[PDB]
Image (cartoon, rainbow, N blue to C red; front, side, top):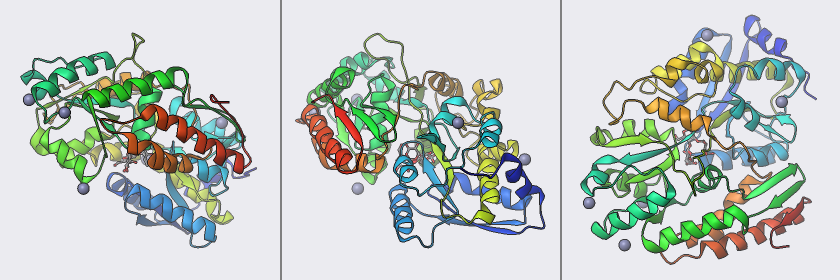
Length: 428
Ligand SMILES: C[C@@H]1O[C@]2(O[C@@H]3[C@@H](O)[C@H](O)O[C@H](CO)[C@H]3O[C@@]3(O[C@H]4[C@H](O2)[C@@H](O)[C@@H](O)O[C@@H]4CO)O[C@H](CO)[C@H](O)[C@H](O)[C@H]3O)[C@@H](O)[C@H](O)[C@@H]1O
Ligand SMILES: [Zn+2]
Ligand SMILES: [Zn+2]
Ligand SMILES: [Zn+2]
Ligand SMILES: [Zn+2]
Ligand SMILES: [Zn+2]
């Protein structure tokens, strides 16, 4: 049990005669680094060796490599709420849970985000951004085809048929071959793929209930030309954005900033709308986001300063303001000083980029509707491998996503059993 208390963390910042060097690895260097520099200016006794690890996929592989070698491990490492699990369960990350930290830091982060940085009773990071889903809609394309901004998956289907019949170079949306994109859709309609009871006890429901119904719907959308299967955040996707290939894009809301940065020519053409409802339920959402974690290898005499850094970067009021000023005036932060500020909720756009100026109100309503009835599996790295090998190849106009979900469940059951997890599946 970690004996680094909330007071010990604060002492690392006030005890300026105690110089520390911290190595910090991050994939989201573009959005984060100016605020890291602000930390260093404020606390010159804590020097930050900031390492941009490149693409997220390369970051996670690099970190696994150093952990297994037990050598050259960073003190602080960027994680995410749906990819940290396998690192936490394998002992790569410091579990810094204790009563003092829980009492103090729980007041600093919105409860949906604070729950998700726990796993198996341990506490593994400070939440960074929250990522409620938004539908980024090419309103110009919909207007041209006499189509309404869709509020439901039913509308996406019905209007999508009309769009693609009239203009076979455009699709209503993309079904993205990315584990976050795909699982976020299921979570946002209340369709559990699995349930976690303890670190060693899991239930897989990938071929039954609401999940199966939603898979059947996604497959019909692919077959009928409503959604196109393809990669996200690749050059193929980047070209499709500029080309207007997708009338809608339902995604984690950091993308709202990405469009402003990479697609200036789309100014005035998009609306930011709520993600869609399903079967006449009120709409729900999903939020994942990044987190900053401490490695299990971090030396004991560096741990208080490492924790002070992650808490400052992710919740200090000056840091939160820096996150806004250095990312086009908005970044959607989990800190309560952002989430509880009614002037963030009612913040108006002023750059003219989106056709609606109430973008943050849309993001905050979606955050309010996040489906919290959800856990990620202990082995999320293996989940992404199986998704890539088994599910992604069926994301096409003739695909059998239903059969692929059942085969992926079988592979995950075998992996769970081989690694000592108790597992049930809906095929048992
Ligand atoms: C790995 C990834 O981390 C989290 O998503 C990242 C966001 O938190 C961050 O703000 O923005 C990144 C993109 O610039 C996201 O990664 C992309 O990574 C996201 C992060 O997502 C965000 O927290 C934030 O840092 O922005 C980056 C993109 O600039 O996430 C997508 C999945 O949506 C995909 O993995 C890309 O390769 C990443 O670059 C989580 O929220 C994600 O679900 C995921 O775990
Ligand atoms: Zn707790
Ligand atoms: Zn058209
Ligand atoms: Zn077609
Ligand atoms: Zn390419
Ligand atoms: Zn401050």
